[PDB]
Length: 57
Length: 70
Image 1 (cartoon, one colour):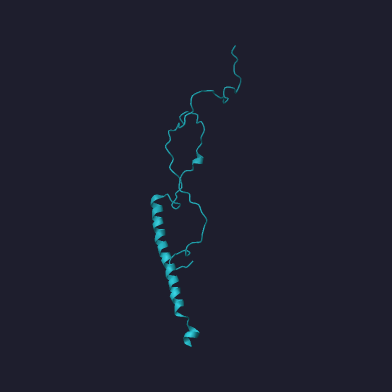
Image 2 (cartoon, each protein chain N blue to C red; image 1 turned 60 degrees about the horizontal axis):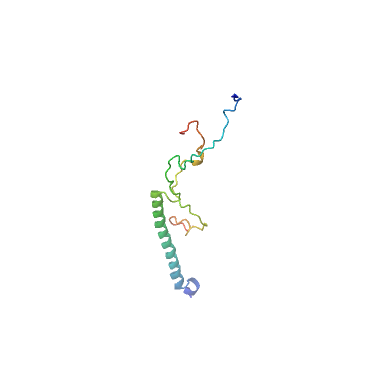
């Protein structure tokens, strides 16, 4: 009583019901380094301007 | 008469010089502090400055790759 599969049926993406636990870290990755402090705030005018040699602004 | 019609009082110059000295001292300390901050940021790289670009991780394709072991 075997029915031969039609065209395009064996290439379908199917789902599998399994009790095998999903691997938490299949890549065996380490801990990612801490990103930079990403400082935030409100801009203020430069203290005494450019402070480049004799320029006052 | 000359002092009245041509020149201001002694305090004027005194306090103007005090303000000028204060401003220049702040500028000098800020210059040293900026140089030290530049050195530290270039040496360590944790600061906002001297941030050299790396590969963007959004370019990575996370999908099955026709082989189970990538």
